[PDB]
Image 1 (cartoon, helix red, strand yellow):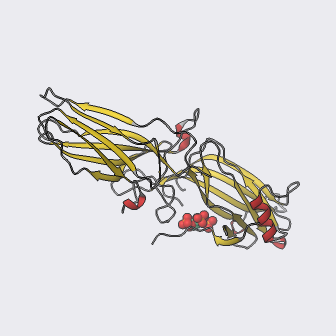
Image 2 (cartoon, rainbow, N blue to C red):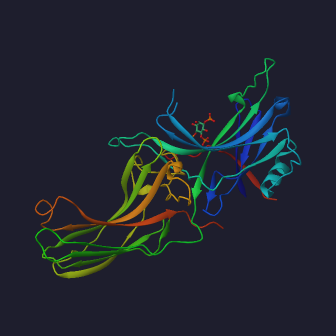
Image 3 (tube, rainbow, N blue to C red):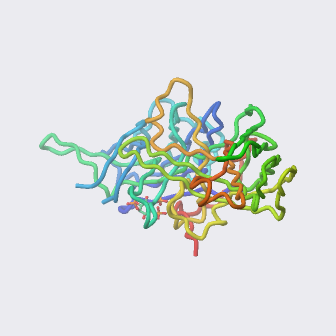
Length: 364
Ligand SMILES: O=P(O)(O)O[C@@H]1[C@H](O)[C@H](O)[C@@H](OP(=O)(O)O)[C@H](OP(=O)(O)O)[C@H]1O
């Protein structure tokens, strides 16, 4: 039982069928977009039907318009049939087998230098405007005029906004560890803090066990130990926007008295559903959609300029120590340290077809 997504143009002449709404990027390769286009012969007679894959960065309110920077464009012909227009994939030949003699296959690939689906809409107290990276699979019909000018009617076009989702690679970095120490004003003794995680890559919805070791040699009391998951977002194309937002939070029940040590392990789960406010964070889809999760960690391929990624997303554990009698008397700064990590989806890996609309389901 395989669900297949379809969309018909306004004039009923071109229909797209795709086997997936989200295509998988596991660093090594990127899943190609294979699908089929169903044409009405009488309506595409004398016309040519193409399918294009565009990836673009957008900044501003969409409609003059806003800011757009194209990052990858590819276009393929689907009608009339090109060469031995037999299927390339089992999905394609099964779809042609099911849909009939007017179905033509297409396959558009992703290069190895593109970002994944990332979008953001600012909050009231945020300065920058909404921005994102869109992936558009669009099939359209083209005809000519006796005044030597080709036309592309929107009514003969179908536009799909797919997602390029980031999945974990085969490898994984070293275990993330950090040690920080503070020597506060007028005190000889140091406050020390060691933080470790279990692994370097976590999956969306997987618990993160932050292990914390506070070594308090000072005369002061560590009033509180707070552990956070912070998402850091850098718009690196049109405006140099910057966001730090808290996605998970956990307080320790214990205090660390002067001249003692404490080792605890707190567990956090960074989830979009944790946050009632979905504005101001980096997502992989629109706020209105139930498909939407937090954006995955940006993975920059070696040799590629980070500005071509449009929006950079990173994640870090943050440990905040509230020390008694310090703030307001000995400092106006925070006592905290960071441990970076990466957040993705897990590693990857005749049918009967059920057809559904490509339009993504709203949240409500
Ligand atoms: O119909 P058009 O002119 O081609 O453009 C569509 C339109 O902007 C819809 O509002 C949008 O629905 P969403 O709110 O779900 O984004 C859809 O995205 P879609 O590809 O998911 O259908 C777009 O493609």
